[PDB]
Image (cartoon, rainbow, N blue to C red; front, side, top):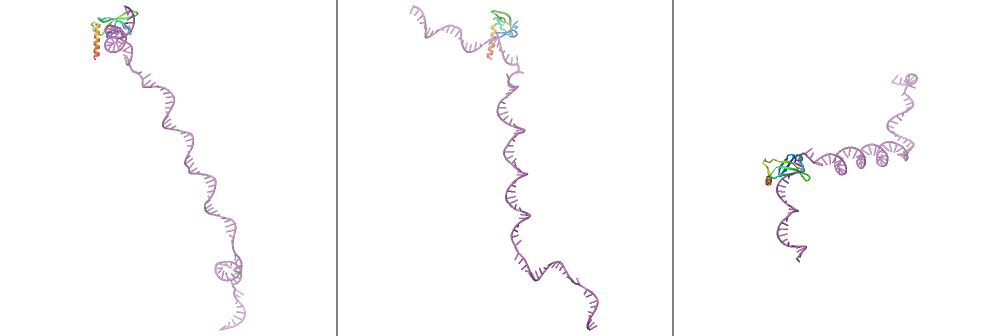
Length: 83
DNA sequence: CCGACGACAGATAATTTGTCACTGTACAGTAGAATATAGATGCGCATCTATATAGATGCAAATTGAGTGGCCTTATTAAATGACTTCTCAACCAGTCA
């Protein structure tokens, strides 16, 4: 998205050098223990090329695990269904 | 004895439904409006028509005044009245008488 943003687990990620690829599709890889930095790849002829690191925005400093981001999302969905 | 088909039971992905996360896209002053036409209706102005004449003229009775034409006893006498005409109208000398 414009400015080099990606959306993963309802968080917004800003790529370090990603803004030249706005409107392009990319693929991405993450360690479930810490999703605060995500690794973005261009898909190509039978091969993925590493493009940038990307960082989570608007979250707390403490490192965010994948299950914790699901937890925040399902708690928020439960409030929406309640209200 | 060997092979094929049906009953009953058991396990399984396709189908449908639900939930969840990421996303393309509209919100951005804006199509009711412009421009022909036919077709019917109404007001105005002209262009006839048909009726209505009173004045003038011709004519034909109806007197109306003004003409014209046709038909008629007469002679004597007398009186009366009214007229006309004619004629006439000297002057002194000579012879008686109381």
